[PDB]
Image: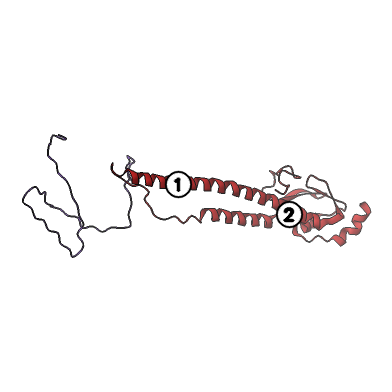
Amino acid sequence: KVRDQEGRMNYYWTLVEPGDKITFEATGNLVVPRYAFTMERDAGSGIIISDTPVH
Amino acid sequence: LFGAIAGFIEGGWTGMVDGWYGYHHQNEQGSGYAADLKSTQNAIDKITNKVNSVIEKMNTQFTAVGKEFNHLEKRIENLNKKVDDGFLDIWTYNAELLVLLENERTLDYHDSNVKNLYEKVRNQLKNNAKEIGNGCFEFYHKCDNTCMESVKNGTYDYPKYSEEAKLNR
């Protein structure tokens, strides 16, 4: 038991290409999407983990 | 190492502020300092070029060195650490050695410039003057401000003052 819960929830992600479709089929145990993210990428950057103020 | 700066010239001149290498003349019209502007400008250009070469040859590119790995990806994290440490070692060794070597190059470059000025003046005066040893030249012939302006310029008329210098030599 962690955070008062004895069950678990695995979180999965995927990227759907332009013109492609995603299909969900389920008889239970599914946490359906509500909000997806239309996203456009670049070369790539990092994640700065700091307490420094942002100006 | 040529032996002028801290050599047969044992000290710099604080009074001479209009250049890097220069002359100090003592005539019956007075004493004065006068920098050699051409040599100073040449030195400025070459040291500027050296600074530009050291600074403006890096060719940096956009990157993000930080990477995140989970508990089961320790080997790849170790590989990333190894890459980072190798780059750090290479760059620190190269930077230190480069600075140490170019400091030598610059100091000997200045020392060569001073010597070259001294030899140019000496070859230009020949035996009309006496070499004291401190880096100075005592004239055997009395010559005025125009004469030393000519010596600085490089247009010393040796035949003009030769007969005058022969009697006092």
The reply, left or right, for residue A38 in relation to residue B100 is: left
Q: Earlier in the sequence, mark 1 or mark 2?
A: 1
Label 2 marks which chain's residue?
A: B
Which quadrant of the figure has residue B12?
top right
How many residues crowd around disc 2 within 10 Å: few (fewer than 14), some, or many (20 or more)?
some
In the rendered image of this protein, does residue B145 appear above or below residue B8?
below
Q: Could you tell me residue B159's position as x and y percent?
A: 87, 62
Name the tint of chain B in the rendering: red
**Residue drawn at 9 percent across, 47 percent down:** A29
**Helix, strand or loop status at disc 1:** helix
Residue B62 locus on image (x, y percent)? 39, 55
Q: Are marks 1 and 2 in contact (CB under 8 Å)?
A: no
Chain that bears disc 1:
B
Residue situated furthest bottom in the rendering? A19
| B51 displayed left or right of B69 | right
Q: Which numbered tag is attached to residue A3?
A: none
Instruction: Label the purple chain with its letter.
Output: A
Is residue B110 among the parts visible in the rendering?
yes
**Which residue matches tag 1?**
B86
The residue wearing badge 2 is B116
Disc 2 element? helix
Of the residues shown, which amino acid type is indicated by label 2? Asn
Residue found at x 92% / y 55%: B166
User: Where does the image place residue B48, in percent across and percent down from the top left?
Assistant: 58, 55
Q: Position of residue A3 (x, y in %)?
A: 16, 35
Q: Amino acid at mark 1?
A: Gly
* Same subunit, tags 1 and 2: yes
Residue nearer the viewer, A40 or A24 = A24
Residue drawn 23% across and 57% down? A39
Q: Nearer the viewer, mark 1 or mark 2?
A: 1
